[PDB]
Amino acid sequence: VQLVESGGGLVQPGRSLRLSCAASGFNFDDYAMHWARQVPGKGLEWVSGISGNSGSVEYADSVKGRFAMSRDNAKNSLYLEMNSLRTEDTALYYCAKETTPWGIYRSGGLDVWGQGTTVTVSS
Amino acid sequence: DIQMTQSPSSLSASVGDRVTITCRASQSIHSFLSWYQQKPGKAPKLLINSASTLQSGVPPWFSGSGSGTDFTLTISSLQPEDFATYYCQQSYIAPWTFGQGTKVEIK
Image (cartoon, rainbow over all chains, first blue to last red):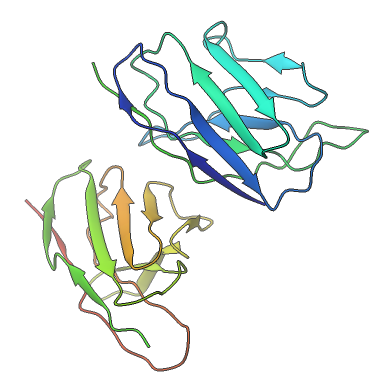
């Protein structure tokens, strides 16, 4: 259960950046893996995620309509695309799979955190 | 094993500044490197273990990274409690050496 992320960089607000989160030591299942970000000086938060059996998309209030998503189960990796970036997206992206998508009571997962690659925006 | 050295031996920073400290190894040491904290006249404190794992009760603004021979520590924002020393060791076999550490002072 090791997750390695790559694809960050320093870009202007408005330019897309395709990052990655590769899952290693992960037996294949219907894991619903989410995202979060950290600002220096405060606590934790949560962004969005996608459940199994394809489909099943959801986001937060302020991240709808500008996040592109695609999942490939063969490569054990994730591709995520940005669009119409702003100044509050200076984030170190964590993927968290919650590691228990059971058939009954699929919710209430125990989040496990990765490493992340920093993305810096600057006007 | 461990023949350790680090640079710089002293640092000057204010509250909220992004500070760093680098200690390297002569050869392959893998990645299980720790980071320590020590106040003058008090017990030492632990911040980072295995250069990637954050312990319970340790605030998340202490972050470490590095693999192979080069290692580094990253602090997003300094705190009034953060003015102390740092160390990095390894426990492959059992001889016991020590480093020289570093210092952070008010500028």
